[PDB]
Structures are given as C-alpha cells and as structure tokens.
Length: 128
Ligand SMILES: [Cl-]
Ligand code: NA
Ligand code: NA
Image 1 (cartoon, rainbow, N blue to C red):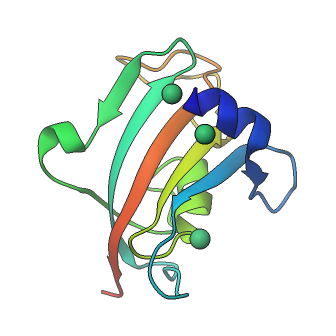
Image 2: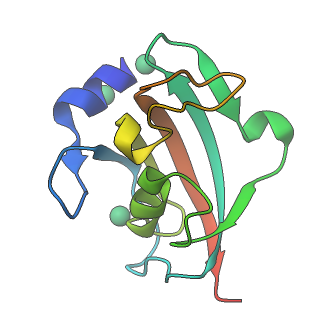
C-alpha cells in the first residue's frame, strides 16, 4: 500500500542523505514557488503508524493545521518536507523516528521509535 510504496520508492529529501525523510509527490501543485522560512503554512494531513492505525487527521476536524515553517513547531520531517512543497501539492512522507518523535514518542498514540507515514496537502502559505 501507500506506506510500502513511499518506503521503497520515495525520494530522500534530507540534507544529510540519511533516508530519514522520504517523499513522493502525488499531486503536482501550482507554479514553482515553495514557502519561505517563517511563513505561515496551512496544511491538511492524515498520519498513520507502521501498524496501520491512523493517529491524526485534520480533515476530520474540518480545519487546517497552521504553523510557522522552519521554526521547530512541528517534527523535523515536516519542516523539511513542507518546505519542498508547492501550493496545491499533495505528497506522501515517510518519517523515521529521528525526524519525528524519537525515543520519547508522543502520547496518547505515538509509541517510542515510531516511523510515521503522512499524506499532506499544502493549502496555502503567507509571509506574516
Ligand atoms: Cl495504502
Ligand atoms: Na502507488
Ligand atoms: Na515540490
């Protein structure tokens, strides 16, 4: 399924080239501009654990998730991954724990040492 496909066929987008964050573009976005550090970015997403369980979804909340890019307000895989996206793009990301929640995990749903799968849509970005 989709997690296996990004694991086996995804592009390493890390600067270290350590395969910690793998990406597949599922829907090409608009234009060529990607967000800038510090921009307010608006995303829709759904996350799955490696045991198949969905652990989060913004769609189910009927509102986007909003954060400032490149500031450590989200896991490192998101700062790196969203920075690669164009407006309107949908991608899949496969995030090793060193680029996610590490050995700590994150209650209530994310265990220690968890590899995470996300589908992310970049809805908009704005320089505040
Ligand atoms: Cl799937
Ligand atoms: Na596929
Ligand atoms: Na892109």
